[PDB]
Image (spheres, coloured by chain):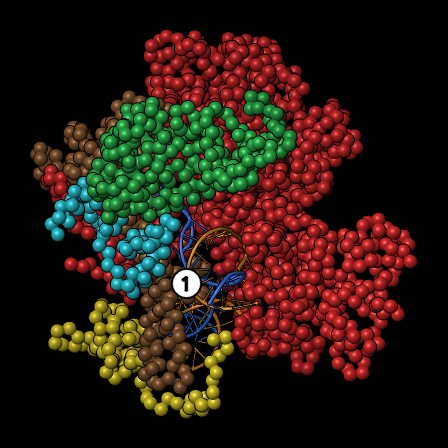
Chain colours: A brown, B red, C yellow, D cyan, E green, F blue, G orange
Amino acid sequence: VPLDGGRFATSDLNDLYRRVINRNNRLKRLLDLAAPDIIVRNEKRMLQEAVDALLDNGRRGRAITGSNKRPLKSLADMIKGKQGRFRQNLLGKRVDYSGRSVITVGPYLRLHQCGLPKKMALELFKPFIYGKLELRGLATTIKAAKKMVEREEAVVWDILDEVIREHPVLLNRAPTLHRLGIQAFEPVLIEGKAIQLHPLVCAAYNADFDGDQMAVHVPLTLEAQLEARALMMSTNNILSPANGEPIIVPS
Amino acid sequence: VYSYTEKKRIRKDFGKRPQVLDVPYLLSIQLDSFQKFIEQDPEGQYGLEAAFRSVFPIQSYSGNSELQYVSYRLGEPVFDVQECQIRGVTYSAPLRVKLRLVIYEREAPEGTVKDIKEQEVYMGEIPLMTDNGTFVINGTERVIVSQLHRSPGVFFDSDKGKTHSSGKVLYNARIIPYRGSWLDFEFDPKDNLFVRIDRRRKLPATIILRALNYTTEQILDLFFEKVIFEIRDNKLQMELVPERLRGETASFDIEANGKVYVEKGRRITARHIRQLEKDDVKLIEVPVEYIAGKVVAKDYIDESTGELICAANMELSLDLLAKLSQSGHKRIETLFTNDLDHGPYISETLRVDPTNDRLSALVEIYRMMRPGEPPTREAAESLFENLFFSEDRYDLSAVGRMKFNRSLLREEIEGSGILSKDDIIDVMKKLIDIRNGKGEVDDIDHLGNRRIRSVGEMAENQFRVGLVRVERAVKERLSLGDLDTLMPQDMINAKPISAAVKEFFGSSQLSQFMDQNNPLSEITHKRRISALGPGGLTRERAGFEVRDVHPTHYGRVCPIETPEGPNIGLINSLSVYAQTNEYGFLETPYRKVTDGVVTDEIHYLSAIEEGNYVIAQANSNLDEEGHFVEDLVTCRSKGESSLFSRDQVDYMDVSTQQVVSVGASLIPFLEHDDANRALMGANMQRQAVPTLRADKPLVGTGMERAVAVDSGVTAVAKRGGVVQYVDASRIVIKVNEDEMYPGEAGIDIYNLTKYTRSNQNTCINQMPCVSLGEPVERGDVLADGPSTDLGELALGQNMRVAFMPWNGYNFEDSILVSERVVQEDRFTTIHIQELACVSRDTKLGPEEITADIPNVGEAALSKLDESGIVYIGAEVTGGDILVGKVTPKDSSLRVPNGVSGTVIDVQVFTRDGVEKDKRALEIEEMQLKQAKKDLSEELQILEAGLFSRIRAVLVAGGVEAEKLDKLPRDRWLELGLTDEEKQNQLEQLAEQYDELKHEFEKKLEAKRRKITQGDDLAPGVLKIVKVYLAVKRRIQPGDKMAGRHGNKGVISKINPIEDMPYDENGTPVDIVLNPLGVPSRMNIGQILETHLGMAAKGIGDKINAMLKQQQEVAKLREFIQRAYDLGADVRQKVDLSTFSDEEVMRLAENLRKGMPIATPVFDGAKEAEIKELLKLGDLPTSGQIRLYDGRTGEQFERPVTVGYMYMLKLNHLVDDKMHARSTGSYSLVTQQPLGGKAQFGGQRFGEMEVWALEAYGAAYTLQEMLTVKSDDVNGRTKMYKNIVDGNHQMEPGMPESFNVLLKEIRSLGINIELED
Amino acid sequence: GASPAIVPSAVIHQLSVYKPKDIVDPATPYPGDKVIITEGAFEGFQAIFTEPDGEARSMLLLNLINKEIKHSVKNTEFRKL
Amino acid sequence: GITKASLATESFISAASFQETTRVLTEAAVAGKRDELRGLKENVIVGRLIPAGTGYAYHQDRMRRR
Amino acid sequence: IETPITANFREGLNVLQYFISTHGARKGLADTALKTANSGYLTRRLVDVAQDLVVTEDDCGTHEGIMMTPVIEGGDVKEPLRDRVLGRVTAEDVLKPGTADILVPRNTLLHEQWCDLLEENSVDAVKVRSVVSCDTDFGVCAHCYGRDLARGHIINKGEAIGVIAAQSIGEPGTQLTMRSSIQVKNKGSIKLSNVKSVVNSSGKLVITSRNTELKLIDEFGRTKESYKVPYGAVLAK
DNA sequence: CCCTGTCTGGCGTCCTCTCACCTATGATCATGACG
DNA sequence: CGTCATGATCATATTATTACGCCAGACAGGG
Ligand SMILES: [Mg+2]
Ligand SMILES: [Zn+2]
């Protein structure tokens, strides 16, 4: 990675491989020009310890470091634990077509719908709007449609009301504890910059309104819209899966 | 009497306890510690002189050369604070040191050096502290925070219960040096005694007692008493003192003097001990089985054979008695090894020892230190003398020697920094005494065992580490060169010293970035007692007890102001009156209650002196003399509260505000809030934001003026006098003559700090609050700062609140606000963003900043000038061009997508050599013109003050009333006047005037040099353009507002004016809260604050009514006097009969928007006083007005509570959190979207959300949620084509990060594949 | 190990007159070697060494297609293999 | 116990996504152990349908065509 | 502390009383912090040990299930039979004490009407089919699980019940905490279980067993009191 | 070989936001000035 | 014209410990 300062603060792996190749080339040269009897041994010890620093740093006695106290990262520190490929990149991923803001009340909602801003609904639902523009014939190519929805002209709000209409979104509170923590709503466009969320539903999220933040996701494909309508809609989950108590208790 | 800014708006003050010690200067920890650090300090310690006299003289490797120390000196900084923050340099001062080199001769190191050389040398740059208590490291104002750590000295801990799973407690005795090797004595379940050094391998403890050259006979002489057996004609008689027999069952019938004393099968009672010591029984008779297991003390040798009869510390058998009996020994010395009294811990320890003399012990210690190498007697002596017994590698401080003498019951608190033999032997004696059952262990969290480091001591330690590295270099270049030809600047180099101190002030765990968006946040971030950092504990490891308030935090560390979350109780905040002791502990004031009378002398107690005495509580009633009016008074004796008698008390608290900190003493009615809600209220009061026009608190605590003046945001007058010229830029004070120097004629100029960027992107402004011609006193505010008003502290604004449920829009914690609030522009905060653009140096050539730019037209370039940089004043949108930049390819700086603003300030810095373009020359001419005008006005204004002094002197003694203004004004000296003090004073003013002339010449030349020169910059950058956008963010549904008690809330709907519940007068309420947050979240103080705020506004409305009708000053005097008396025995006692009919009109001009009321923390306004003040206004007594509705126009039943609450806007806004992403950039190593908001990123669909979608039957939603939308690149381009063509369908593929998992597992020796 | 490897009285005597070969080294700057470039407009590829200058420059082997033009460079200028 | 019952599986990807990855991958490396994606979390790793909801009908179809 | 806080929040609190309140409050906050730190890891380990168990058949075809009786600590009956045998398929078909008369067949889901008909006849112990005693290889059949919780009908073939089970156990882990004779109340018949008793000289019944459990059978069949009886205790009955 | 103590390996919540920081020191070579 | 001094540019890895805690399973100590 460049740090935009004329220098490369390198990753730890290139440092480790560079140490192994330095030590290995010096050992090839020392086996070339003959080792002094009981001498071709210290260099092989150094090579073994450099490879043991590369494959799993810190498992052998005291680990190495580049700067300054922190031990640098080997391969087994990229597979294991947190900050590794199993728990940070493969089981939970960062996801396109998503957004997040601060929640609020708005009690004029039916319980299968939530308020969602015009700016968030315009930025989540961009390629739907592109498809409706070049399907109705208001832009020739994709670039004219992109510049139309960047300027936000007076026709794309009608396009946006024609793409929101029967299309669920997934609302998500950030510590998801049980399976009612992800639910699916049908959006209503709001002038403003917050997510208006039905009050009874906030019994299941364990969410007050003292600065809580919720994240919305969009189901792209068709089967995911049917799963966010038949399986995950806010009217269906009125009973908890822990017991038979209703979760729509008026608070 | 009152100061003149205290006759502007005198705050009404409830409160009953008459104060005796005012609030000290709140920034005394930082300033006093760093003043202790850097100052010319004789008699050795403390300061830099301690390091320079402990690491010097560097003497060489037997080359008879020596680099000794003389003195040091800091020159002036090249840059003052403002130029340093603008440009970006450290605010440092060069540390010149006078070092001396001496070089001894041959055969006489006690002989004469042939040559010396003493000279000045440059080393390091230590950063100075500004007057606010902060450092400027790289243009960013940073604070070093005090650390709370363990006090050096002995410490007798007890590893209770958990070890060995049998309840047998251990006891360890950690000696904690200030610098050097640790030392832990402990036990084991076999009751052996084990030493260890720096948590290494374990040895039996007496191996170090042989290492101090003790024979075993002397060791048993120290650690045990003696039992004497005399062989006198019958059964080997015994000397017996019966105190050892207290509860022991004898094995025979103890008789003496022909009298049976003790029977066999019974124990010796205490009265039998009294019988035996009253009859003075000395010699008793023992059987042959009594000395069957008695342990001998010293070695007995047979005189004939020359052999050893029995070794030392050995039990005696029949044959050993038979050997020593026939050798000629009549005295036998043994030891007393009881079950309860004295265990044989030393004896079992010596039986586990394999060693036998000093040499073997030193070999074993040298072998446990450095494993597996040949020891030598010289190497073992050198190591064991350099562990504990050398001035170099081991040093208790004075704090360490005090705790080490105090916890061993010594007398002298002075000693050497190194240990000795008596010290370790007293540690082992006290450990054996604690194991025996007498004496107590020491807890950890007790604040007599927690020292407070600060900026000075930590900077001294880092500077000392830099000096030991440089002595590791000088011991190099000193005995490996030719002498005499070198000077002591070729040897010592400034790289490790400056690297060490620059790394500490630059990036440490305690040198942290100052949370600066509020005067309160500054003055409570500088007063912080952090437990973390180097030498302390860590957050994710410890623990339970250290996150808990000990009984001795009372009046030292605040109990209620601490950050909730992962570190509660580790980021403690220091209290109000809490100083720091001479050694580093905490101390707090008290009042010496002599036998009857509370004497008004203050008297500082530490944390261990508080425990022995008995302290009366702060609010105890006393009748005008000090006599306690009750005969049972609530006190606390030894960490435990109780009820004591009237005149067994020894101290009383000073004031009732001293348990709390300055964060949580601005909360009115603190005693009514539950402690959780007071914690959340203090923390959110720290997190406020400055509004556009900050008002005042109607219900304060009187602590606002200490927090405002004792911080550094207001412009406090230095010398009092008369104002001469007020302006939005500057303020000129003419100094009064009874405060004024004879020379340096003197009228002061305060250059205020106008609109500039804070660290939290707020707008640190200063507004002048004085009129013209106005008197000001010494120690008084002239210019209000951010969130100040007339010298008070106004964080948020005070608004009309009602507690009622209103149609669901305030459901959980939400807040509902009228449009009358946003129309008045009263939360409209002003933010400033800094946007930088560098001109780097790459291949194909350098870059271009000029406006001849491809791919753009008129509509972009109309807002730029002819040289790329945007104008000053051009109001831009989100996504225009500010700086046009093209590389050998458009890379112009743009406003980031979303923010508006108005460009207020443009800086251009040029690396020297590069051609300045036309706008950089425009800024250079501009700043030349500004600095030229400013220094010329300095000369003109101070010359005007000097000529006014000449006119003031020439009033008498040869006065010329007409002849004075006929001649030009620069010659007012050669007029008719003899040799007096006046011609002497005119000569001194001529000296001052010619000094100002030549000083103005040289300073204007230096300022032209500073403007004209280039600046040292990054490697390979041409010029840096910085542009300051100034957004004005108003309020909207989604911001966070909160009061001062923990009542948070997202504002949920900004209603119109008409819908608000109004009352039967006509006025709409501004904010409708929710009542249901009160009985669960027990913050009942906000309702008393609401009622007292309504009382304050009732008095303000009556003043507005009595003044709008143009009434004469008599009725205003009547009503203001009635509103200022109104209470019990209070402290205020003002009278308006000494305000003289013009101040009363101006005081009523300041009271007409409400009357400010002080309510101190635990001595506040009771309920009956609020009722009597609500009766003075014509408001209802219960505080509740009946309110109509805005929609229906018909009355709400059961009348509701209205009043004024002082609510704060927090800077968790909603157009800083809101974010959305369709398709942006993707990361490089794993093809997933980036993280964050500045990087246009997507929200983490974490692991528990994957579990929650497995928990439904949603399968396609999860498949596209982790294959199509996230990772698979061909899958997502197929998806994007399919979405813009209307075909909702996914082609799945494989995550590319799983292929990264295959490459990382495959890059090992592991062969992972994919079958079939 | 804790102490230095037990050095017997044999290798010491064997290392009393070693280096009986020639230049050898790590095969860097010699008569018929390879060396990659690092600076100049003729960099990006590799080159060969022959007779260098000494206390000034060296000898770069620049060639494209079927022609070659020598360009003396100091070894700092190039990238010693 | 549940951490030992989850580390002792016939599927090394589940026991690798749980606690210590070094011991699980070395034991499955020298044993030549062969996962067959066996349930939910391995299919969350590899990027295909969960065999729980709608993917359960898909997996019955896929296993019936084996 | 032996001297309590005699002041409420409507009146004032002086300095020491507020300090003692601060002891309590900061102890509570540190409990909540480290409590969340343990609770999240408990949910992780449970959803990683279950992780895999999918309702993969429709009838295993066994009989052996567990016995559901109402729990009796020794006071009031804490959890009754309706709240334990709600919606779970019976193991052996329950015969009312009109023996050889079937009340429910042996594969009937016990919804609310059947639970009321269990409460009326005062049924002793409805032996019921549990997940732990199933027979399905590589999964769990549908009848041994029970009602689809959060819905009304029987469980659908497929819903991953290991994950919803592990979340339902670990989700209230935020709420949890971290750091002479036998006296009867009701009236009924007297039952003894696992007792070796004998007659004393006084005419009473004395016990020669530690394993004695006393029970109070009520008027209709079930038990409302149970008492562990020690070794060598002396009964008056 | 049968305990019983020691040792060293594992593990210790989620999501988001902000900020700084990411060398300097020594040696060698070249150029300029002075003798 | 030559030598010396000063300034600028380019080049590599200690420089000469202590304040978590539990569980668990293997490795080894004692008997
Ligand atoms: Mg909340
Ligand atoms: Zn079954």
Left or right: residue B931 compared with residue B1126: left
Tell me which residue sits at (65%, 18%) in the image: B1128
Residue B425 screen position, x and y as percent = 70, 62
Q: In terms of depth relative to the viewer, which is nearer, B1188 or B631?
A: B631
**Which residue does the numbered mark 1 point to in the structure image?**
A58
Name the one closer to the observer, B334 or B188. Answer: B334
Q: Position of residue C1 (x, y in %)?
A: 47, 75
Can residue B673 be seen by looking at this rendering? yes
In screen coordinates, is B177 left or right of E77? right
Kindly identify the amino acid type of the residue bearing the numbered disc 1.
Answer: Gly
List x then y, in percent, for residue B1051: 37, 26
Look at the image and tell me in which quarter the N terminus of chain B lies.
top right
* B993 to E15, vertically: above or below: below
Q: Quadrant of the C terminus of chain B?
A: bottom left
- Taking depth in this image into account, of B630 and A191 the one nearest to the observer is B630
* Marker count (numbered): 1
Seen at 61% across and 25% down, the residue is: E6
Please give the name of the residue rendered at 50% of the width and 25% of the height, measured from the top-left corner. Answer: E185
Q: Residue at x 22, y 75 (%)?
A: C47
Q: Nearer the viewer, residue B96 or B199?
A: B199
Residue B732 appears in the rendering:
no
Q: Chain of mark 1?
A: A
**Kind of element beneath mark 1:** loop
On the picture, is B419 further left or further right than B905?
right
Report whether the residue tagged 1 is closer than 8 Å to ligand 1: no
